[PDB]
Image (cartoon, coloured by chain):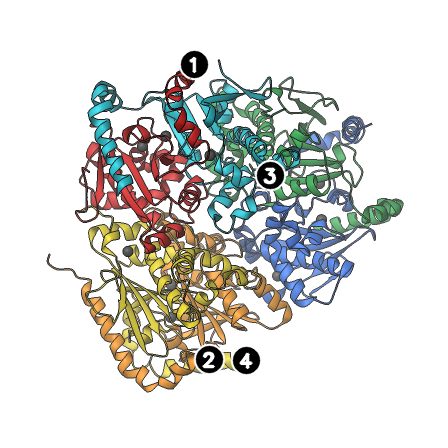
Chain colours: A orange, B yellow, C red, D cyan, E green, F blue
């Protein structure tokens, strides 16, 4: 009986689907026919679930190019630490799809990172988030131990950057990655997407900093 | 690398193109995200949730893994449950879509599960969370083969994830209150359409705003 | 003392009930062929064979504190395995989740954080019914005392039915129409059972 | 449904019958349970702990699973450890009985363990908590087969659970204190008798 | 760096001295290890099992962790069970010694367990495998404090580990078969002495080849 | 007499010999340990870390398991991570050495992993934590066999554990600060020498105080 305020969102989404069907799909039938025969992505793109991040949009990629993992905080647990989807998706990308490029892309104003900086406060209302963030506890420990001089937005920014670097260390513990890095076949990349400025900063191992590509 | 070079050129095209003509949207979004849909879909590079729904940046909070699987509550400690909880509890999302798709690699693997152990051991382990799909399909659709069998696995996998979602505390509590809807979508890549599960009918039909994927006889709720 | 009573009781059984039911026990010795999987609480006030006046051999029984079945893959104790054996090996096609009034596990659930010190294993176990706790705290925040416990008993049963639906053997058999699930509340003081009815969305006298 | 209909008719029969004849007992029990025994037994439908011990409602706090197994402390996160902890710590029980039984399906499975993984994967994983039974039986009773081997597996499984119980904090502490006792029982269905493990004789013998 | 320079100088002394005088021993050992004792002891730098027993290389197969703890069977997936299994099954070792020691940091932590969660979260979780020791000590020695309390915890921890070892399949089976014995030793660092648990006596006494740590009353075995 | 009789006689020789000449040291050590090195090595009886480095009691805090394996952070709940955390956080150690050795039984097992399931199931499961070694060796050294293959597995196993160590919070934070160093050593039993990994060179060389195992291209740090 009466007002149920969630319904407009679904109507809108279905209208948007019809617009895709009538618009982009209708002008790209050959592309979708070709793709239906198989995916051949060349990039594994790991990024946050945050609704403000669209990997295809910011890279102006066409459908078929990016095999994408999305979770809160763009975290890849150390090998063997977790039995969710992250390790399996990465493995499929590298072993079945033969991808040779992995990007860990974090972003400004990340909610997972804000949470990480107030971790104990999450237990009560966000218990699964609290447990999940333990897979990036190395970030938290490094940030709390070494960056106390920072506050506010500067501190969140450092947490976003350090979290990406933690995931690169975590990735190095997976068998498929360790083997292929020996082979010399595979490259890892760390990116920060700055939402307000529409830009990406990439980690440069010589400068030990995230800088414009 | 040519592929990385293409992405960097793409970044510039975005900044000079779409970003430049949507600066106010991005400054607004810089203050916070307010999505109204949790969209769970496959990592498959052929699937773009924002594209297929013509969503604007800010609209869809997205989980992507191989096979668009959500383990039952307490079964796993990866990203899935946590991202869903963040969406529902922190972001107050009230619509969840489990979106599968045609020709899904994870589903092909599920139908040849034992063969995955050697080269795809993590995928083998992960697909344990959709074992109910495999059991149901092998038991009840034993006469299907080839493309038809993969199509059934894609569809049934979505239905399994909907059962798995209903074991999470945030979901269970909100369904009692009647404040949340669950949807199951199959994106057909070549055909350019989506099919949606109508849980009253117990079948997939074209999307419409008054269906959802819950099966009434399994509500198990008081008043 | 109470061990002695049990030992005397063994004698009473052998000379009484066993003596007058020799055909039954000789029959049972060839195999178990239960009809029902009965999931209930460890509470000493609950006796499923007694309240249903079942014959020995009819009920394959799982008993734990709170009559909880964790979601599939969440736990590696006895519950899932016993259910699987019941359905796959023994071909049982009826499952009853039976809760009961005044359940200690439910009292604990409503004071969960306080259990961590002296009952750490109970604290961890009750996490498998956290969906109950969250639902009850969110949606019955104005209920108190006995009333709140009674609601937690009822809602706990329904949570377990949801959890059962995640198991492969259950999911597959429900598809085929070869399995039925039931939720029961046993009211100790009144000697009655109320059964969940999915059309009424309520627990009703059968 | 005829099976369910028969249960319902049994409920009414309990109400008008045993319940009506024991109103006082149930009113009293409505105020709390005060069992003095923790009874761990198999889910097997042929086993009824209250029946075989001629116990009254309220006497036995009961754990039932396939094979009457208690995993070692920390090994599992299902119901067993928690129910035992509730019994000992909250209900102050000071007697624990592990009761196995003849013809146990879990034990038949244990003796063909690898064959179970395909159709009974959860049972395969669960029986690993009694792998010490399997190893012991394979290494030390190689000259038994068939029903004799199953019977020895039933007996040995009980002893393994006693060892497993001894790893739980509440049990370890209270055994040291001296205010807790453990017991191992085998219920022979076909004979209507229980044999209890005797540490002096190192065998299961009739109680008296 | 200076620590490393000094350590590498010590390595050079080993090479020049003991190695050069024992080349044949090391050649022989290179063909296979044949130890006859599994020695479980603490990681504490004050404990050296070969030194205190004046053993030769090749004699002791050694497990070292903080607190000399062996989790119950199935409780953990670290190295302890696997190392023990290799010792018993592959190397046919018939003697296990659990050796604790005075002033053990793990035991000090155990007695203040809750205080460890913040800064030593992994130690906190690990010590749960000896929670039976903590519970026993808090329940049965409640009037002890300070060093007396730590001393009791050291001793009781050894007895807990013996219970935990008895849940492992190889141990359970070989105790019954007759090819295994268990021992529980306390090394008192300040005095250079060891006491051994005599399971018949239920007390710690001088070590003796005739005694072992199993209590006859708790055998739980069929004969 | 028996192995146990020898050990017990050895206790008395220790007390009346070495303990006497180091009586002041042991009195000092009874007040607290202050090691400066965390030494991780195999349980193998042929390895004695204090002997091979001619270390004094109090110098080396030691972890020993089969194969000298450190699981990745969060992957395991046995003793390894806890012991390392105690060493770094409670004892402020600033040097970690992962020491493997020639002819390692864990490495022989790793190369015949499937065969271990039946009689060494716990070892099979434990070796999962060094699967990255097995994958690398099978993929990249597929043409080696016999002793040559075991030798490469011993070396690559050390490198895997160094990657695993770098996932732990205490290590990651201290590496940022620059007050911790990681080393990878191979102890060659017959030959009486140690080889150390120089992470700049990406190869094993004779030990020296100004190398360590860290690979500069994988520093992944902000400065
Ligand atoms: Cl996306
Ligand atoms: Cl549903
Ligand atoms: Cl019962
Ligand atoms: Cl050592
Ligand atoms: Cl490195
Ligand atoms: Zn984010
Ligand atoms: Zn897919
Ligand atoms: Zn109850
Ligand atoms: Zn049974
Ligand atoms: Zn110690
Ligand atoms: Zn070794």
Q: Contact (CB < 8 A) between labels 2 and 4?
A: no
State which chain disc 1 sits on. C
- Quarter of the image with the C terminus of chain C is top left
Q: CA distance from mark 4 to mark 1?
A: 82 Å
Name above or below for residue A161 compared with residue E5. below
Q: CA distance from mark 2 to mark 1?
A: 82 Å
Secondary structure type for disc 2: helix
Which residue in the structure is indicated by mark 4?
A: B1
Q: CA distance from mark 3 to mark 1?
A: 46 Å
Could you tell me which residue is drawn at 84 percent across and 47 percent down? E26
Which residue in the structure is indicated by mark 1?
A: C4
State which chain disc 2 sits on. B
- What percent of the width, then of the height, locates residue D39? 42, 26
Secondary structure type for disc 3: loop
- What percent of the width, then of the height, locates residue D199? 58, 19
Q: Is mark 3 within 8 Å of ligand 10?
A: yes
Q: Contact (CB < 8 A) between labels 2 and 1?
A: no
Among the two numbered marks 2 and 4 on one chain, the one whose residue lies closer to the N terminus: 4
Which residue in the structure is indicated by mark 3?
A: E66
- Quarter of the image with the N terminus of chain C is top left
Eye-nearest disc, 2 or 1: 1
Secondary structure type for disc 1: helix
**Badge 2: how crowded within 10 Å, few (<14), some, or many (20+)?**
some
Residue nearer the viewer, E125 or F21: E125
- The numbered dot on residue B8 is 2
Eye-nearest disc, 2 or 4: 4
E155 relative to A44 in the view: left or right: right
State which chain disc 4 sits on. B
Residue nearer the viewer, F56 or F86: F86
């Amino acid at each position: 009986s009466g007002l149920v305020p969630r319904g407009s969102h679904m109507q809108r989404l279905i209208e948007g689907l019809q617009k895709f069907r009538e618009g982009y799909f209708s002008s790209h039938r050959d592309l979708f026919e070709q793709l239906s025969h198989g995916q051949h992505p060349r990039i594994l793109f790991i990024c946050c679930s945050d609704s403000r991040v669209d990997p295809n949009l910011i890279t102006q990629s066409e459908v078929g190019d990016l095999f994408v993992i999305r979770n809160a905080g763009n975290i890849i647990p150390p090998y063997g630490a977790a039995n969710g989807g992250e390790g399996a998706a990465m493995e499929y990308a590298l072993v079945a799809l033969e991808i040779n490029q992995i990007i860990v892309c974090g972003h400004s104003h990340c909610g997972a990172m804000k949470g990480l900086l107030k971790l104990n406060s999450l237990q009560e209302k966000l218990p699964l988030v609290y447990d999940w963030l333990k897979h990036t506890e190395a970030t938290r420990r490094l940030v709390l131990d070494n960056y106390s001089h920072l506050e506010g937005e500067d501190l969140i920014e450092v947490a976003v950057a350090e979290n990406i670097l933690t995931q690169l260390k975590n990735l190095q513990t997976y068998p498929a990655i360790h083997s292929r890095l020996h082979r010399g076949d595979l490259s890892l990349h760390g990116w920060i997407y700055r939402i307000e400025e529409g830009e990406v900063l990439a980690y440069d191992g010589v400068l030990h900093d995230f800088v414009a590509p």
